[PDB]
Length: 325
Ligand SMILES: Cc1c(Cl)nc(C2CC2)nc1Cl
Ligand SMILES: [Mg+2]
Ligand SMILES: [Zn+2]
Image (cartoon, rainbow, N blue to C red; front, side):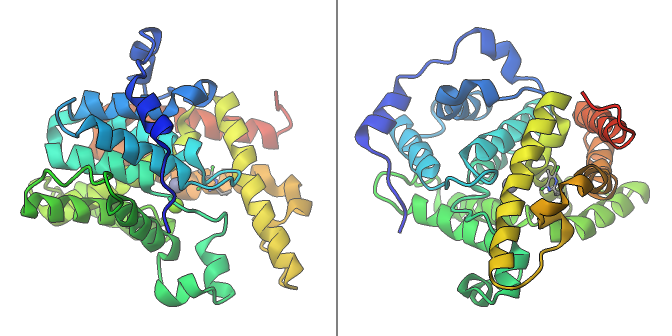
C-alpha cells in the first residue's frame, strides 16, 4: 500500500549539500523552512546527521526512507510534507538545545517520529472519522489517525531497502519502535490536556524525575505537542500564513460534512471566517500557551518557543481589536 520513491529521487537526495548560510539559521527555534522547498529532504538528512551522526544510518537506506515518506504525504492544505519537516525541525532545535538529557536511541526515534507523525493524513479529523463511522474509527477507536500514522511508519520501514533501524540489536529495535509509537500517539491533542496536567503536578510537587521512564514518556509527549503546534512559535507573518492553511483544511472537511447533511462546528465552517481571530485567541489560551509554559518549566532552553507564542497571542489580540497588518 505504501508508495515508493524512484531511484532518481533517493540518489538525488544523496548528493545534496546544505548551503553554508543556512547552517547558522537551522539551529534557531524560529527558523522557517518555507522559502527552501527543494532543500526540505536535504534539511532533514542534515538534521539527522547533526543530531545522530553520518554513521547512525546507512545513507542509501535513509535517503530512500525520507523520499518514500515524502511520497506518502498527501496534497492536503496543512497535514502535508511541509508540516512534517517543520515539526521535525522544531524537534531538532529542542534536541540540540537539551542534547544529553536524551539517549542516542531517543534522538533518532524522535526525529523519525516527527517526520512520520502525520503520514497518509487524508485531511479529515478524528471527529469526522468517528462521527461518520469510517472504517478507520472501527479499527482505531481512539487516536484514530495517530494509530494510522504509526501503522504507515512501520509499513514504510518494512519496504525493501527502507529499514533504517535494522542495524540496531533486537532489544534496541523494539525500544525505538516503542519510542516512535508513543511519540506519534502523543500528537493526538485529546491526550495532551491530561498529559500537561500530569506534568504540571509532577513539576510543582517536585516529583518529576527524568530517570523515571513513565515521566520521560510524558516529557517526550509534551515535546511532540510543542513541535506539532510550532507554527504558533514562528515570526507573525509565517504564523498567519500557516493559520490560512490550517483553516483551508478544516473548511474542506466542513464542506464535506455539509454535503452529508451534517452542519459543521463554526471553526470548520468557511461561511464563519469572521470567528477565526476569537477562535485563535481560544486556541492559544487553552492549548498553546499552557503547552509552551509547561515545556519551558521542564526544559528551560525551550523558553524562545514560549516567548514567540506569547508574541503571536498578542498579534491575535491586535487582530480582534482591529489593528491588523
Ligand atoms: C497549530 C494549530 C492547530 Cl493544530 N489547530 C488549530 C485550530 C483552531 C484552528 N489552530 C492551530 Cl494554530
Ligand atoms: Mg496529527
Ligand atoms: Zn501534525
